[PDB]
Amino acid sequence: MSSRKSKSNSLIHTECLSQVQRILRERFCRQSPHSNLFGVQVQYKHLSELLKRTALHGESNSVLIIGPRGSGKTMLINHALKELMEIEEVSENVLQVHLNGLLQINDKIALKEITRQLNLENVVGDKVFGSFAENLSGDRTSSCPVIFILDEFDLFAHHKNQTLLYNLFDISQSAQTPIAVIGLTCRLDILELLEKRVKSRFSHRQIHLMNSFGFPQYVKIFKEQLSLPAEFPDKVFAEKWNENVQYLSEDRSVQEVLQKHFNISKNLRSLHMLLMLALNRVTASHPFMTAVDLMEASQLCSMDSKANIVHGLSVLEICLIIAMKHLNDIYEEEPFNFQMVYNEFQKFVQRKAHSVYNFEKPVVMKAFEHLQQLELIKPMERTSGNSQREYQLMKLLLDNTQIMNALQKYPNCPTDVRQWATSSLSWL
Amino acid sequence: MPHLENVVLCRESQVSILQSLFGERHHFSFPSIFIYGHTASGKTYVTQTLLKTLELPHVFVNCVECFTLRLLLEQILNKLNHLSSSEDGCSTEITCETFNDFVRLFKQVTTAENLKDQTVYIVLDKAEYLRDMEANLLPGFLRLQELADRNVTVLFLSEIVWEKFRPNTGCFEPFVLYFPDYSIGNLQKILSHDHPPEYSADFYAAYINILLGVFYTV
């Protein structure tokens, strides 16, 4: 009696990792209640005192939340709305309209899609095309007040005098039921982005939800995302999970990766890719973690994407990008067409023995056209329609630094070609 | 197997990457996966074979065939109702043009037991002509996981690099995957695998090596 529990334990190890992938991936993009606050305890009390003034009473407030995107700004507004769910004597009388400014681009469409969330006078069908005129606005009604939620104040911010935001600012200042409005935006200053008729009619209340961490308190964020709650069927495997992270948190190679991404982008979204890529490597043969599965996942997402595209080329297009590099040193910032590159093509054929390396003529335009579909050249501002294979006045989209460092790593480099690229053309 | 690995013998480090992101049916992933390659044919031929092997719900649409946003969102639903349930939906068409109604009608289709807790793949062929239209359809697929709230993974098979379609107000930063280039030691073996039955293996592979050294520079 021994060949039963050992074989059954292997099946649990293959199924326990499946329950973690459906939580970590549903935590970065999708907002999960397991994620608590991150140094925003003082801002949590400010938004809590404003929401109770509308649900419990009838005082509507409109604030502006400025931060990153859907991974950082959605950690406080949605948490305050879910706090209203515990008290069932108000959650059943207050609905919620999920709006998004990224979808709406004009103003006529917004007057019809608003009825798709309330559904108090129509059906699956939408009523007459009439633009809404009476939007229902003694301060005590039984029509279930609904709070609207906006997002992305950038698309409709530059429409036509913003005729949509002025309606929401008048319902709370009307005479029937006050309706609040809480939105999300990434751009900092938003107040001055409106006209004077809307600027003088605002609450002028905004909070800058910007993280201000460093290095000691930054490690706690890396360990909090990997701290799964008490949901595993076996509590023995849950103790070794949190303990293994502590052994890797203090390491000469793990701490170097954390500080490299923190200086580039300290946003929480930039760290989401550093936690899910390492989970993909953990399959059915990785019982624990180490400092090897986390270093290879950070290099593939940080290599020079503008220097590795030249390795899968031949010699024709490789000699072309070096030809315009030599012309940039003698022509100090000025456009030039393609026919000038053909003048030096028949110049390198000299000082060489008679062999089979010489080409013809139509291969030159075919080798240069391959760079057109790669977007390596950019016109000054206009692409002539009647331009042929002589008038292009194109330039370059690279630099004089990565072109020289991409020569020793290129596979199979000829000896009579590399010397021509390093020199400044001193021979004929 | 006959067209997944025999076409390119240099994908040993990429099979374990795509299969790790798939997992099971109830497993999720990023709402957008940008994968750019070369020649616009190497990454396309491997996609038609890997998806037809594991038998997964997936479609194929193109942005070059249609120059309007009304026809792009229509062809996606035309290839979805045929595999949305176990039977056909009596061959019914969809009349829509509003971009806001696209996320509303897509949730009603993904309600059956076939697309309830399963991963849906959206392969966007030739994803380098989206900047000609409007600058609002780019972040629509990056935040589709939050709006639609469905297991939808949008794939990209474009020639342009990722750092060229950056909008004015920014968008979501996904995972940029780069397939390895055609190695010199592996390109010789893939060009000799499709040998005709009139010859053999060693006798046919000798006629390829004599042409590779003269056509590698051109």
Image: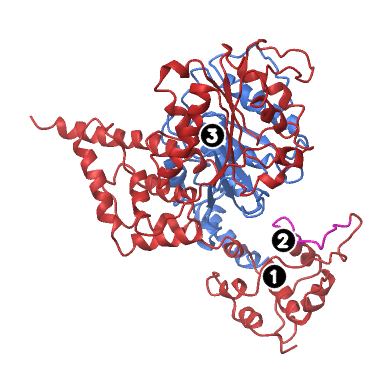
Chain colours: A red, B blue
Camera-nearest residue between B151 and A189: A189
Name the residue at 43% across, 23% down.
Answer: A85
Residue type at mark 1?
Answer: Ile
Q: Do tags 1 and 3 sit on the same chain?
A: no
CA gap, disc 3 and disc 2: 35 Å
Find out whether residue A105 is within the magenta segment. Answer: no
Name the side, left or right, on which A323 lies relative to B181: right
Residue B115 shows in the view: no
Quarter assignment of residue A417: bottom right
Residue type at mark 3?
Answer: Gln
Measuring from the top left, give residue A424's x and y in whole percent: 69, 85
Residue B114 shows in the view: yes
Name the residue at 29% across, 61% down.
Answer: A251
CA gap, disc 1 and disc 3: 41 Å
Q: Is residue A125 above or below residue A184?
A: above
Question: Looking at the image, do the residues carrying marks 1 and 2 touch, with CB atoms under 8 Å apart?
Answer: yes
Label 3, on which residue? B145
Measuring from the top left, give residue A60's x and y in whole percent: 58, 28
Numbered disc 2: what chain? A
Q: Do tags 3 and 2 sit on the same chain?
A: no
* Label 1, residues with CA under 10 Å away: few <14, some 14-19, many ≥20: some
Picture disc at residue A371: 2
Picture disc at residue A321: 1
Name the residue at 83% across, 67% down.
Answer: A393
Secondary structure predominantly adopted by residues drawn in magenta = loop
Q: Which residues are magenta?
A: A369-384
Name the side, left or right, on which A315 lies relative to A208: right
